[PDB]
Image (tube, coloured by chain):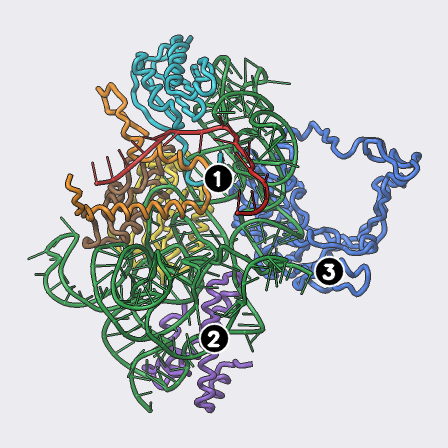
Chain colours: A yellow, B cyan, C orange, D blue, E brown, F purple, G red, H green
Amino acid sequence: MRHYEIVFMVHPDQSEQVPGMIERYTAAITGAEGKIHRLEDWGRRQLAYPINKLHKAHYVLMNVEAPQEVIDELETTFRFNDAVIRSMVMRTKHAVTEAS
Amino acid sequence: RKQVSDGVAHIHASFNNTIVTITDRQGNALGWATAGGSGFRGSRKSTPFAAQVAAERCADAVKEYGIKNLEVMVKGPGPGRESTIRALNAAGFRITNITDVTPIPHNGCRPPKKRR
Amino acid sequence: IKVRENEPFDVALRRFKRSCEKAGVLAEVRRREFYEKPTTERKRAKASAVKRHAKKLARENARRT
Amino acid sequence: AVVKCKPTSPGRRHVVKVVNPELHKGKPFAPLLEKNSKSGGRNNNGRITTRHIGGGHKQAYRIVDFKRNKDGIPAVVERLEYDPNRSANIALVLYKDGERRYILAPKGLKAGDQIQSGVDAAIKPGNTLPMRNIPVGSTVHNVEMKPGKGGQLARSAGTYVQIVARDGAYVTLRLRSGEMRKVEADCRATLGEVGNAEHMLRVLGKAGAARWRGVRPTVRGTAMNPVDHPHGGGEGRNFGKHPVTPWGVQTKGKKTRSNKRTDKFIVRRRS
Amino acid sequence: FCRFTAEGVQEIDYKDIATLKNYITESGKIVPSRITGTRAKYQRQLARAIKRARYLSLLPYTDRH
Amino acid sequence: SLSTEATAKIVSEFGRDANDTGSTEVQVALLTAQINHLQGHFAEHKKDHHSRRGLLRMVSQRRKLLDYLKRKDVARYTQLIERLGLRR
RNA sequence: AGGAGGUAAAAAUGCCAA
RNA sequence: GCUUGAGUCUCGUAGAGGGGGGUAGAAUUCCAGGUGUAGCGGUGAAAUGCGUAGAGAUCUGGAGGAAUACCGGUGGCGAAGGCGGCCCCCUGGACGAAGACUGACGCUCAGGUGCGAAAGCGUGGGGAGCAAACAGGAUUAGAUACCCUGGUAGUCCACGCCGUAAACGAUGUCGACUUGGAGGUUGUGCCCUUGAGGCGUGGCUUCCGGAGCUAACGCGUUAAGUCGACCGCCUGGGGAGUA
């Protein structure tokens, strides 16, 4: 299909409840037969500028491949989730796993 | 009259005039002085010497608070940029650091077409 | 912007203003944009820099100084 | 869509009408109809209270739903129906158990679109939820003031309300007048804006087209006699009387807001 | 003279800011290519990686936050 | 896009073989596959005048080939347009 | 060799032909 | 018939090409307040204006619109007009290498049709900033101007219309041929990648300059050189691109 390089920051209070979210998204794509290749967790790291006056947040890295239907509903799950702040999706540019 | 150790000086050196203000660490304005109130009017108000004597009228009226060490914030090019800091390196104030907060935009809010 | 020169500096040492922009830049953004003169005043300034190069290796002029 | 007509006759010249192919072209759904006694603007004493009203053409009240109490029950839009009582258009909906009901139409609503209400519903125009599950900055319509009363705001044709901010136990709404108002955060609101946005573009065209809307000819005050209006009289269209109502109260800028019971909720006066 | 990954092949990445902080300045702006000596291909590719990394707050915009 | 999957069925359906990607009948079937395809693209936009010019080249490229084929090989010319449903 | 900042209050007209 | 002109297909590269939908920071203005005190603002100077009803300066918070610093460059792209934060979706066009195919399918173009900056016009939204008109202050012999303070249309968005510009490398389009040099940009091959390479081979672009040409200035392999094919137009200045 097409690869996508997803990052999304989440609210640092919901890092207590973060890994159950990641299994919903990874079963959304793998249930739609798209594969994942990375699952890199950057963790609770310090920001450089205060997004919503909030300091340090938690970062997730995906680097997955999926058909274009799965990402559009994925954006809405990132749109309506006040645990998640400032998500991002990029285009194919064929992917493999590295780069901590 | 409430004494304080650490203050902050805001220096606003606009082209026509420079207005200095010494505040606290939390933005509550302790006192201020300006180059229009320092006797000079117009042309003489546009002078680095008028800027240096403006902070000397702000060197007092902060003596009720007794600030020893202070930060310095500058904004605006003016003539008053590298003059009022020399109005405090003689006036006995431990300058911790000097920063600059000149409001550079990122290309918004179109400027005027000023004088031809 | 930010300078400390940490403990015994005793004097301004403020190279940092012309080191990046902050004197020269807002005496440019402060007025008329023209939308066109930015193409025009880049034309001659780039024309001058090639004329600056035109006399660099053409320094083989004698004049008997 | 919005069409213009060709000047075959004077009165057919300036007429512009909206026409809509997806409107149901038959009888309305019979058991959701009552009658409605047209009054002519008179009340139980029998005097004219609101002037310039009366006549036109018979109508039939369609009981629309406003409360949207069916929760956890998906439903299916049957067809978009014309409604002469509203200014919007309505939709006959079929709930999954079998009930048929009338709701206002969101603008992005085709026949066959599946909606749901309650609290479990998703953000999709046609759904109703209590406004703390609705994310801040959304566009809702048909929102009620009291928690469960009905819906009174943004229910005319092509109107909407932007949710400004959720202030804990309350929520701030900017109405269509340009007025920011607090409502209780546990009120229902239907997502998306009302359809029939081209109602604004409609021009009647002839005097009789106003008549069958039920209105009557407004006589302007300066033609009446001085016993009949505060203006009026003279010898050739005089004036000079600081324009008022027919009961001698200043119009053209004179505020009549005197409530004192809802100033708890009005954040900013409209402008 | 002192160029970069043109023979050291890269696909310049916006996540590893350790190489990205070399080509920003101390004030938080993107350095010109004419001083760093990078090629025009691998300097447009990196300024894209800066504005990406500015969006994730890995690098500031200037300081005023 | 008219993908490598999409075109490979068209060159097999019309060519002398799969290596015959150059014929007049192959190119016209490539154009009408794409001219019909962008009719969905040029409905919602209707104001993208830039990429519309690339369609008008694909139209005019098709028109010049049919006038060549009609001048050349009339039996296949009246074979193609009823295999495609075009020409007015 | 490279580079930065600063630098004018208004001020009109003079016949026709040689 | 044929392949060298045109065209297709395969693998890829580069890009402010276009349309649509999101999204982010800096800044201005505004709104509510905290601290705080007499000016601020502007200018050649001043005044109008603003401010003790508490401004301006400063701090926190909120709203709103518009534009995208740095990168950024006689850099890239597009037929031209034009196009600049970032992300997605739909989508045009160019280019490169080694092969394959069709077989002159080509060039140009009156009328015709399409696109076409800015300003205008229409409807419905939007309105921070900026600013025709307009008002006030100065200036001046006068100043219905520059300058100052304001400030509506307008600029913004969606959809129609207008169809003009110093719409300009003031240079129609296509092809072939004829010394060089220094760069920019984007491919690609080979060689020792052995290090910012070495030698080529393509596309595009900037400057200089020879023969030649030109009234001269200057153009000068991207011609204004040497020719070929079509098209547009000119015939003293005004009157007039007007009736």
> Which residue appears at 72% of the width and 31% of the height?
D257
Location of the C terminus of chain C by quadrant is top left
Q: In terms of secondary structure, where does tag 3 sit?
A: loop
Q: Name the residue under label 2.
A: F60
Label 3 vs label 2: CA separation? 53 Å
What chain letter is assigned to the residue under label 1? B
Task: Please state the chain letter of the residue tagged with numbered disc 2 in the rendered image.
Answer: F
**B100 with respect to E16 (left or right):** right
Q: Could you say which quadrant of the image residue B5 lies in?
A: top left
**CA separation, marks 1 and 3?**
57 Å
Tag 1–tag 2 contact (CB < 8 Å): no
Q: Which chain carries label 3?
A: D
Q: Which labelled disc corresponds to residue D195?
A: none
**From mark 1 to mark 2, how far is it between C-alphas?**
46 Å
**Label 3: how many residues lie within 10 Å, few (<14), some (14-19) or many (20+)?**
some
Q: Residue at x 38, y 45 (%)?
A: C41
Local secondary structure at mark 1: loop
Of residue A11 and residue B19, the one placed in the foreground of this image is: B19
Q: Badge 1: how crowded within 10 Å, few (<14), some, or many (20+)?
A: few
> In which quarter of the view is residue B77 placed?
top left
Pinpoint residue F1: horizontal percent, then vertical percent: 41, 67
F39 sits to left or right of A71? right
Task: Give the camera-side residue of D103 and H228.
Answer: H228
Instruction: Please name the amino acid that badge 2 sits on.
Output: Ser
Q: Residues within 10 Å of mark 2 (few under 14, many from 20)?
A: few
Q: Position of residue D93 (x, y in %)?
A: 64, 57
Circle on res. D28: 3
Q: Mark 1 points at which residue?
A: B110
Residue, x 33% and y 36% (percent of image)?
Answer: A48
Residue F18 visible in the displayed image: yes
Question: What amino acid does circle 1 point to?
Answer: Arg
